[PDB]
Each structure stands twice: as C-alpha cells, then as structure tokens.
Length: 149
Length: 148
Image 1 (cartoon, helix red, strand yellow):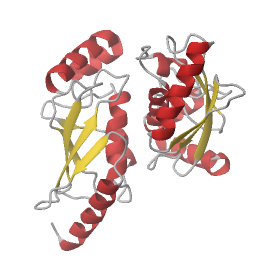
Image 2 (cartoon, one colour):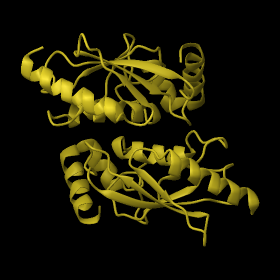
Image 3 (spheres, helix red, strand yellow):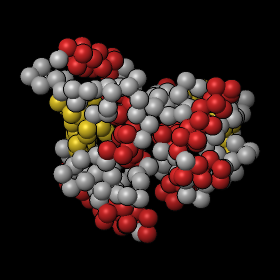
C-alpha cells in the first residue's frame, strides 16, 4: 500500500484492536495490513446464536475513498451474504464517506446479523424465506450455524 | 412477585458488569419493573453523538414475553411511534424465554443502524427513509441535535 494509506490503516487497526466492538475480536496481520481478519459472535436471539463467524475486511483497492470489501469466511445463511462469502451492506454503500471508520463497518455487519435486509438480497433463497417463511429461514440458518459456527 | 425481582436484579448485574457498547442500565428499587436506559447514537447514523434515554417495562410474565420499550428521548425513526413506543414486532420477531434485557437493548441499538421502513409506526420516517434518504438523515440529525 502507499505510505500515506498505510499510516491511516495502522491508526484504524490500532484503535479498533484496542477497543473492539462488543462480540468482535480483531486480529491484525503484521505482514499485510490490507487484510484484516475478524471474528463476530452470532448474536443471541438470532439463528446464528452460539456460532463464531470468521470474516475478512480487504483494505486494499480504493480505501478510504470506497468502503472496504467484506467477506465471511465462515459459511452462513444470510440474505446479504453471497456464495463467495461477499458481504453487501446496502446501508454502507449509500451512507459511506471517507470519514467513516472500520469500527462502523464491523458494527454495521454485526447489526446486520440481527436485522438482515431481504431486499436486493445476494442469497435470494435466504431473502425469499426471510420474508415469506421466517421459521424456515431460521431453521436453515441455525443448522448451518451448528455445522460451521 | 419473586421471579421478577430476582431476575431483574440478575439482568442489571450482567449489564452493569459487562455493559453493551454505548448502553447503560439504571435500576430503580421503588419500581423494578421500570428500567431506565441510555443508548448512545451509533457513529455513522444521523443519531450519532446523541444520548437516547429510554425505558423497558417488564411484564409480570417476563421473560415468557418480551418487555415493552419506549424512547424517552424524541427520535425520528420508522419503528418508533408518536408516544415513543418501540414497535412490538421487532422485539417479538425472534423472542424466546432464554433471552434477557441485554438482547432487547442490543436489538434496539442495531435498529438505529438498520431501521425497517415497512409497516413503520412512523409512516413519515419510513417513507422518507426509502425514497429520500438524504432528507431522512437530515431530519433525524436535526432532532438529535435538539433532543440528544
């Protein structure tokens, strides 16, 4: 990364590692800071309860101009998580500016486990069930959590 | 009612010892079923920087049924009604009797980041959120500056 971007990423990761959001543990990668790994506890009162969900934030590309690219490394049944694990946070792409930190990105992803957005879903099956047959969506999400979480 | 008293106290302790980010609970001996709470407005939302007072009213069937929630701080939000009531459909969605006050508050904080415009209690805010987000945020931010 360019030196001036490295400085900002190092500040962002330090403050985030020192004070991580509730239920999130951050594991910075000394050799490569374009690659921030995170684990998110599946919130209680959701089908993901009890599971640990590994995820990765890619701080390369155009960050801070553009939001970082997020991937779940833990398999998950979620309307906003695609087949490659890619996370599409519609709120974040609309709301983003270069002043928003990584704390808000991670907080926004964790909160999306509680309030998934079925509209314009990446996993259409999960989105279709969430709206039309919530208990079926919960069952599948929970079974995937028991295997992968 | 004993199961209330002992559980109320048990929840407070868990929440005073390991408080959720930006959330504080204030128990009241005079009326334990009326729990005062403050939630900090999440960064990146029009509510950022505001301190949002609220209260949970625990029914005598708690935790078989979720508590009922009210914002005491005025807020512009699709799921908060004119009297400050928090839509019972958000708490009820996945409620089970093993859940407690922590999950109710986590869910409400998360709802400030991800409001739901459909079947909104504040139909004004729900509509603006979907069609003109810029005006939605601006209105929520202005009310936050006054009330938060």
